[PDB]
Image (tube, rainbow, N blue to C red):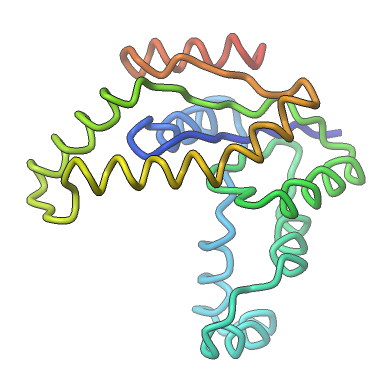
Amino acid sequence: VGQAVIFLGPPGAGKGTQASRLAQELGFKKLSTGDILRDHVARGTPLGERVRPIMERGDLVPDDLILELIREELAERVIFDGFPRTLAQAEALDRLLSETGTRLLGVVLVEVPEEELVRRILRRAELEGRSDDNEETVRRRLEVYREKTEPLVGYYEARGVLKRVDGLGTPDEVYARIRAALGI
C-alpha cells in the first residue's frame, strides 16, 4: 500500500512550498521528473546515456519513460508537484497508482484571487529586479495556466478527489487547510 498527493496551482500561489512542507513533515517523497532525469544524465548512468540523444535532438522525453521513472521512484508516500501536466499523463498516472496499490489522498488545488496573485508576482519581480513581469504578461501567463489546467481539474473533480483550498492567508494557515482537506 501507498499514498499519493498531487498539487496543482497557478504561479504565485506558493503551492510548491506547501508541497515541500507537507513532504518534509509527513515523510512523503516529493518527485521531480526533471531532476531525476538530469541526475541520471549527469552521473552518466545507463539510463542517462539512453535519454541523452533524445534531449540533444531537442525532442521531449516520451511519456512512457517519465511514467517508468515514476514507477522506479514510487515509495509508500509520494507527492507530485508539477506533474501531471497533460490529461494523457493524468490517465497514465492513475493506472500506475492503481497497479501499485497507491491510494490518491487528494489533488490539492490552491486557489487565490487573481488580483492578489498579480500583486504578489509584480512585487517579487520589482524586488528581484526582473523585467519580464508587467501586468499584461502576468495576466496572460495566468490565462494560459488556466487553459492548460482546466482539463486536469475536470478529470479529478469527476472522480471526487479534487480538494480546492483557499490559498490566501499565512503559509501556516494555508498549510492547516491543506492537511484538513487531505485528512492527514
